[PDB]
Length: 205
Length: 205
Image 1 (tube, chains in turn yellow, cyan):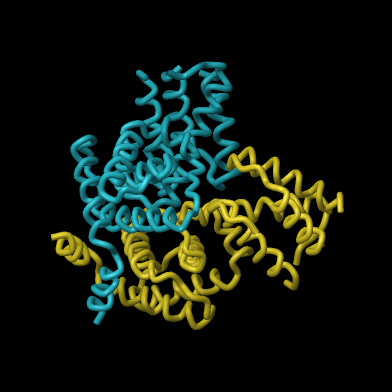
Image 2 (cartoon, helix red, strand yellow):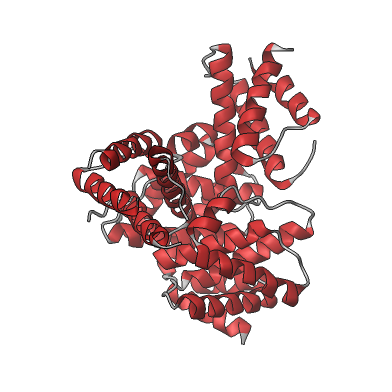
């Protein structure tokens, strides 16, 4: 019964959506080699259809985390950009760069086995940390250890939202971050979390 | 081919998930009578499974917008709460109140024909407006015209993120809101948008 009800929902998903989405997924896997949760298939397919339809209604698609996405998930954004090319050639529809950002986040989601809400929080925490650091040491980030630093932040933030666990100038920076995260997300960094941050901030700078 | 590939993905969705989700949807429709986009079916089913599995791995589920959700989407949060009862009796699993918040947002999503990222932005703008107003007139909101005000904010914010269009003390409040939205979302309120806000803020107070 259950199974049949759901079977019928697939009748509301255009085949071309399934097709272009597979092409994207397939491509993403080659470029990243990273394992993507299979949830990406129905997630992305539902998203593209929605995006295409929304665009066909003359509605705008605004991604409030576009900038962050471009700089924190370089590889994935590159794929998202390509995905819009793939979507243009298969459908003829021109989606905004904002969509490249949304597709990129769907991939990141599948990479971390997360849901959009959490990926958004994870991304904002990463960005806030980068900003606190740059503004604290008055430094300009450019990419070598940047990726390494970012990558560490990504998993640091993920552990922060799921409960997993594991020099003054750098530590004082870390303490500002603690205040930010406690106030915005109601979590207070533990000793190990502070240790982790300090070590890596110190290191990245 | 396309169609078959997707058919196989359903083999990764437990039947009980499909079942409990339908019960939730069915219930929501009676309580709200509002039309829910049918996307809610696969959206919610995928979410519950993910949530249940995440919880079964000992991972925490944190909803950064729980408080906002409780006060801005009263009816939907009520349903989410009930949904956790429904999920407990069908699966025996105790999900946190945070999940009632996530289920509530999935319903709101289906109501507005939106995707999570946008619902999050819409919700944060509504909350910021309420805060700017309360802090501007030094007023305490309690519920009569509150729902009416909130409802207006919800559609105001939605139009703001999709491109749709249409007394000093209240206007000065509206101007602070303009600054906030321009800085955080890069959109500057137009004459009509300011008009709308002023009228309703003035009114709500």
